[PDB]
Image 1: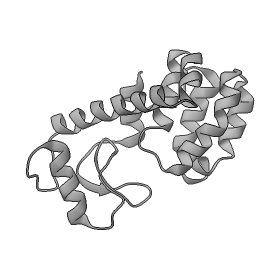
Image 2 (image 1 turned 45 degrees about the vertical axis):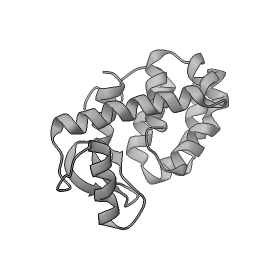
Image 3 (image 1 turned 120 degrees about the horizontal axis):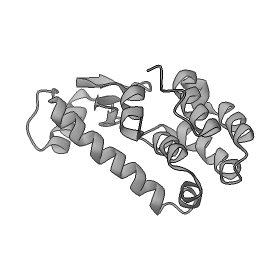
Length: 164
């Protein structure tokens, strides 16, 4: 298991434009295109992302290319953020993966829940951190996905992803 396999489990893979859990146009492995309700606007973003005039449809290779870019962007975002970087630096590699997930193209709710856990996480108060995140808005919206990520923070193991 690793961050790529982890997010592949949590986001799935779809090669045609679809709507994410918040109703936003998305493609591939959870690549958010736009928050606009316009499918045309979504298609425009897709073409710009891929570098060709698509039919709202991409290849698996293209989906994986975007995915790698998005994983990079998440790590970049963490390292450039004054609040996230020290917590990330303080974590082991398994828990780092959980952080990458929480900031992987999530709503505001994902950022807020993880941001509230930052303190307890840096202190390595794992059960307390887990509870804090469990009571977030993120968890309310996606108990299943959030539970897996929280279990990863709580245990520093891949146990929540091993049956998957």
